[PDB]
Image 1 (tube, rainbow over the protein chains, first blue to last red):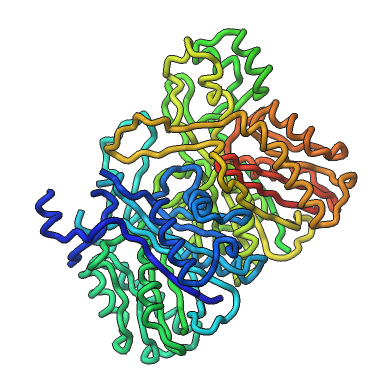
Image 2: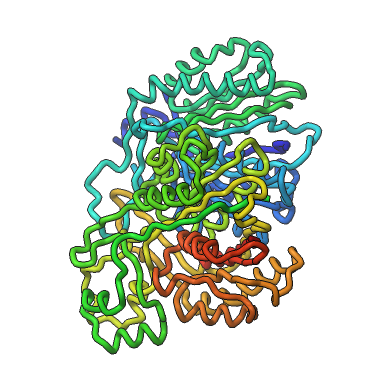
Length: 302
Length: 337
């Protein structure tokens, strides 16, 4: 399976820390509020269009849509079906996964599976989040997308491996995010995080993903060109890269400019990696979801 | 091939009949007779205690029960499960997912755990995704779950006594519940082979048939939380269901006369009859539950699987069909004993 393109859609202008401090290691972010001006669906439509244009694929050529989010516009209809309609994609399966930040890698894993097994040949994969209903310096809003096709396509990036794995048994959640019904009491934390557990466990789990990807591929550590690490903040990113022991690999990060946009991150990384990945160059991507300790990763070869 | 080893369900609390529900809501006998005429759903299960309106069951509680039941029924331990996939419209929280929470409760760990968000066709989506992952990789055994709990969207303590019955007809249609199934790669003697399964969005340019909102912690909740187009559902669901039957029968080479069971969409007692009429499968025995359980969304397919698996003998054939009106998704699957 090849990755033909990846693109992103970020709402509005960059909002630096000065500006955010006034209105009230991550320097800027994009927000979907100026009033809410961009919905998940609007951004997924933009990202999907950009990805399809970059790949030279028309909407009619799409055989499958898979979208990962923690924050869909509504519970139903899904964002996946709504964005497929906006794009002119129809008569195809359209799946939506619910998760935190590894939902992007889950979407890539599901899609890889369905392309290799199936009648589908070309897929549009999306991931993103808009957390405007929950709002401060860590987060951002954003969606990204990628076009995948069966085969090795010259000039593209081969998706050499992908996996996800829950390693949460008996562990308390590391993050929570609630939704409310139309009449119930809402005076409780809508979102929670265990920073102590995240700081200790994310870098260890990121290292285990790297060791697994490398060992299954038979790839050597010093032969890796790029690493696309977890993107929680500038500080956490620096801490994880030191733990990964990939001194030869160039880091592909965005959180310091974009904020943590959850399921969008992997796609923004893919876009930035594909803008650098030459023929034969190798890349690892790692996504660790703290909600219930999901480790995930993938491997690309130019 | 992938085989369905077992299926099981978990329905919260007591069976709640229409007269009990009427007493609660302050309705009269004429109202009960209208429900019988137009709806035909006789009983349902609710995740709330009817008298107090207090929530007694969560989606995760129910999924734990249903999953435990399905694993026992298949003779599979939690440590032997290699994949979990859950379909719902109503997860307990946005994160963590119900899939991961229920995996914890069951003792399942070290596996991919996927959660699909959809209306009623999420169950068949979960079957499709699971089939592909079992066939494509090292995983051999999967637990697949689907269900819904809509207690956040109803209030049995509200004053409905003056309203036209059409205005609160949802109260007689829905039910809360979860089901589960255990799937294994390959042909398994005494199991049911999942011979085909598919899902397909056909809603391009069409208005949603149903909508369901969720709210943030501070936002104004004035907008309608749920909408439905009951006329559009009546117009399209029977025809879309017939189209799914036609496609399944053609792709397998099965004749209508040799079909043993049909598991049709479960929207209400009277709608089921209309749909079965449109399917034109006079030799097939219907496997329905909606008149007893209410429409529990993603749970429906698994409740039907539980019932059909108790009846499906070697060589016997069944088709399931799920049509999701949210954005017009058709889906179905074929079983052979």
